[PDB]
Image (cartoon, rainbow, N blue to C red):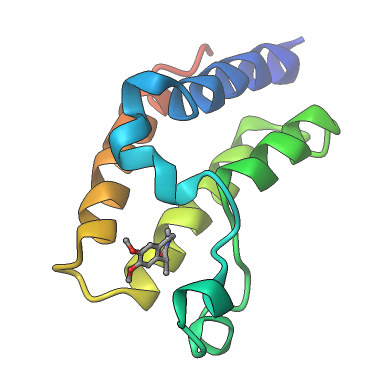
Length: 112
Ligand SMILES: COc1cc2c(cc1OC)[C@@H](C)C(=O)N(C)C=C2
């Protein structure tokens, strides 16, 4: 089916985002933001819907995503949270921009 084939492409992208190739800029997105550990006590007041690649991986593994659009919405939510919370000149935003470039260019190669 088309949805299953598109979800295989999505899983391929997810594997790439978690791969050693991108680890130098992907690592902040590997696990949920630990606001308390980072001293960011305003994080959960500003970010209402946290998202990270471990959560996307669990949702893919559990067949939670019904289509590519639903998968992409979570990956973009993860980047949007970073752009909303952090000053735009922060290193973590530079890392987000680089990983989002990897994501958007490969997502665009979605099979029809
Ligand atoms: C490099 O220091 C930071 C790491 C992280 C974060 C802010 C950091 O410094 C401000 C949070 C808020 C975030 O957006 N992500 C994606 C994860 C980790």
